[PDB]
Amino acid sequence: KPWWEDEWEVPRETLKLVERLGAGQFGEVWMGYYNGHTKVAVKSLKQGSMSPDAFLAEANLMKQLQHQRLVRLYAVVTQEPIYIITEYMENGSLVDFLKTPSGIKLTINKLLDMAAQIAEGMAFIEERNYIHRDLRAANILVSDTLSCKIADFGLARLIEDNEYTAREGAKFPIKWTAPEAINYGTFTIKSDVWSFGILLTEIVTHGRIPYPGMTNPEVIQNLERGYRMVRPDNCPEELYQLMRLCWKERPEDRPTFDYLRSVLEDFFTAT
Ligand SMILES: COc1cc(Nc2nc(NC(C)(C)CN)n3cnnc3c2C(N)=O)cc(OC)c1
C-alpha cells in the first residue's frame, strides 16, 4: 500500500521527540510521545547514511510479526528524516537491565521466568516461518512490569525452503552465532536456538560477555573440538543441560522453541 493508504503512516506532527536514547552511524533513537500522551520509541535514519529502502524494510517486516511477546510497530514517517515508531519498553535492553540494582536483586525464579517469555516469543517466530538471526540479551527489551520482548528485526527473514543463505562477505557476532551460520552463512530457526543458548548464559550471569577470557578464534577452536561454554558461575545444572541441547552439533538435533518454552515454565513453577 502507498503511504497515503498505509495504516501505519502518521503525519510527523503527531510525534514529539523528548529524550535521545541513542546515536549511531545510521541514525538516532528517541523517547517521545504520540499525540501528547502515548509514550513511544522513535528511530530516525541519518539522511544518506544508508538506503531508506533498507531502513524501512524492518518496519515492513514488523507489520507481519505481531505478537504480545514481540516489540510492536507503532507507525512510520516515510518523508525524510524517516521515522520508525515502535512500542516503548520502560526498562530498556535486557543486557542493561540485569546490571541495575533492580535487575541484580532478581532471583533465579524470575530469571527463569524471563527466559521462558523470550522462548515463547521465538516460538511465534518459529511457527510463522521466520528467523531472527540476531538473538541476544542486547536485543531483548524489558517492560515496566518486568516482562520481556523480542526486538530489532533488521536481520530477520521469511523462509520458504528451510534456510536463508546470507551474502558472501557478511560477518556476524561469532560468540552468539551458530557454526553453520558462521561457516556456511546458512541460517535456520535452529541457528536462532543456538543463540538462545548463549542468551541463557547472558541471563544467568546478569549480562556478562559469553565465553569469558576467550577470543573468537579460541571460541571457534574449542567448539570444533567438542567443547561448549564452561559452566557459568552459579548456574542451575538443569538450566545448563538445556543450554547444551541448544548447542548440539547438528541443527536438526537442537530443540524447538516451543519445547524450550514448555521446559522453562516447568523450571519456573518448580521454584
Ligand atoms: C538509555 O537506555 C534506555 C533504553 C531504553 N529502551 C531502549 N533502549 C535501546 N537501546 C539503546 C541503543 C538506546 C541504548 N543505548 N533501544 C534500542 N532500540 N530501541 C531501544 C529502546 C526502546 N525501544 O525502548 C529505555 C530506557 O529507559 C529510560 C533507557
Image (spheres, rainbow, N blue to C red):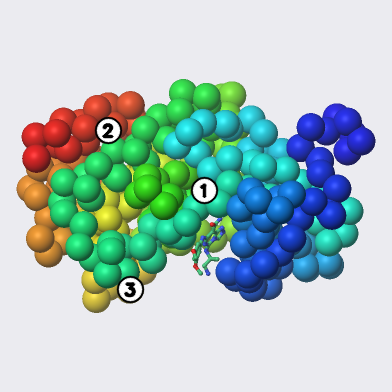
Quadrant of the image containing the C terminus? top left
Examine the rendered structure and indicate whether residue 230 appears above or below residue 87: below
In the picture as drawn, the residue positioned furthest to the bottom comes out as 213
Quadrant of the image containing the N terminus? top right
SS label for mark 1:
loop
Which amino acid, by three-letter code, is at mark 1? Answer: Ala
SS label for mark 2:
helix
Which amino acid, by three-letter code, is at mark 3? Answer: Thr
Residue 120: give x, y in percent of width and height: 37, 33
Q: Nearer the viewer, mark 2 or mark 1?
A: 1
Q: Looking at mark 2, is its residue's CB closer than 8 Å to ligand 1? A: no
**Disc number at residue 215?**
3
Rendered image quadrant of residue 238: top left
Mark 1 or mark 3: which comes first in sequence? 1
Examine the rendered structure and indicate whether residue 81 appears above or below residue 36: below
Residue underneath mark 2: 260
Can residue 49 be seen from the camera position used here? yes
Residue 212: give x, y in percent of width and height: 24, 71
SS label for mark 3:
loop
| Viewer-nearest residue: 222 or 270 | 270
Give the distance between the C-alpha atoms of the residues marked 2 and 1, in whole angstroms: 19 Å
Q: Is the residue marked by circle 3 packed among few (<14), some (14-19), or many (20+) residues within 10 Å?
A: few
Q: Residue at x 64, y 30 (%)?
A: 64
Residue underneath mark 1: 151
Q: Is residue 105 left or right of residue 238?
A: right
Give the distance between the C-alpha atoms of the residues marked 1 and 3, in whole angstroms: 27 Å
Q: Nearer the viewer, mark 1 or mark 3?
A: 1
Residue 28: give x, y in percent of width and height: 68, 67
Q: Nearer the viewer, mark 3 or mark 2?
A: 2
Q: Looking at mark 1, is its residue's CB closer than 8 Å to ligand 1? A: yes
**Disc number at residue 261?**
none
